[PDB]
Amino acid sequence: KVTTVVATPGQGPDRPQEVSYTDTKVIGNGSFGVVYQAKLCDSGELVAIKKVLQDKRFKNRELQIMRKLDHCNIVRLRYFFYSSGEKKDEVYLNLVLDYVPETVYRVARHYSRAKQTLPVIYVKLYMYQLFRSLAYIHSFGICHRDIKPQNLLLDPDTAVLKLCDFGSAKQLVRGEPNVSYICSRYYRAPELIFGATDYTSSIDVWSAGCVLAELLLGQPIFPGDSGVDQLVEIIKVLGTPTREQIREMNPNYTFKFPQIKHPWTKVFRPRTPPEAIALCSRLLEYTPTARLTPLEACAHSFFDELRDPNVKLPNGRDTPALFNFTTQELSSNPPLATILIPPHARI
Ligand SMILES: O=C(Nc1cnccc1-c1ccccc1)c1ccnn2c(NCC3CC3)cnc12
Image 1 (spheres, helix red, strand yellow):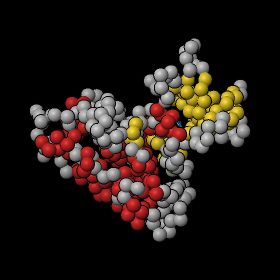
Image 2 (cartoon, protein in one colour; image 1 turned 30 degrees about the vertical axis):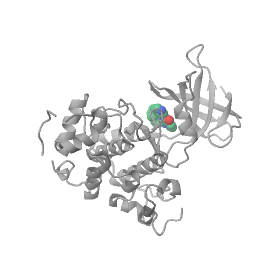
Image 3 (cartoon, rainbow, N blue to C red; image 1 turned 135 degrees about the vertical axis):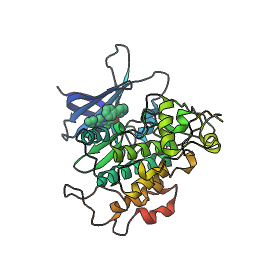
Image 4 (tube, rainbow, N blue to C red; image 1 turned 90 degrees about the horizontal axis):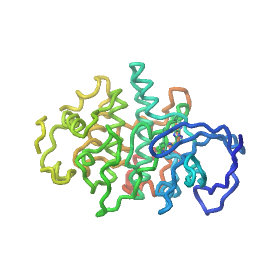
């Protein structure tokens, strides 16, 4: 069964073209809608198709965001098209994206089930690429607002990571309030748990620190099915937030909390590299402004191994693209290019 549509390319002028695809199968489900895998008849390339119900009252925000993004660590919008679907008188928006075969969720789960941890070389590769994608979207004021292992796609052979799911993504403008009910259980910044509506893009940095700690630990660092439980777990590690730290995140919670004074070194297994622990404590900070920015995290000494000219993947292959930064990508701190682009790098 070959399906032919007239799809509009994701980038460039709005000039639709006939796109034919086959071998369609569901690869993802959720409250958002459905993600399919399909094969393009023309090149044989595999693609993913996110199908969502299109609102008649407004333009789709995820599509407007996707059309402006062009980064090697973000899943690319190749085409988009409208169609019918499961509901009779409803219109669906279909986003044709690059296909990526794995997720950090599945890969980390394979390691947990085998009582092994993901090798630190992969922790550095995956986390570095996640921080590059965040530096990129944050350069446009865009916050993803749902960073979690399931949204981090991976090609296991090339070790390329691609951020996906821009369904919660929004441009955060200072002074505009934003819903606090975004972000998934385990990865929510403490200001979100306290119900702040004045949060910044640093909520993505807290989420990324939770993914890093989880990859190091083999399980989530701040588990819990309620905000109280999550905050107890946060406080056990970070200690009790001071009145200033509360004011900096929370919206008027000045506080019957348990009093805890805990060393970050004792949180992880003894074989954990000290630079990984130092990176965690800098991402996972109560005060949103104290957290490292994504570009500062990229320049962290934990990723120095990635900058070594002789670094190779365990499978023998070369590392993926890591130093092809743009002016846009570096704009939050241009002097960091001196660390970020190593002498051997030609990108
Ligand atoms: O954009 C995507 N997915 C999403 C977009 N919005 C919301 C949710 C999702 C989602 C993310 C992960 C899983 C299920 C759904 C998406 C893009 C590209 N490849 N891809 C895959 N590959 C197959 C790998 C094995 C799982 C799976 N999902 C994708």
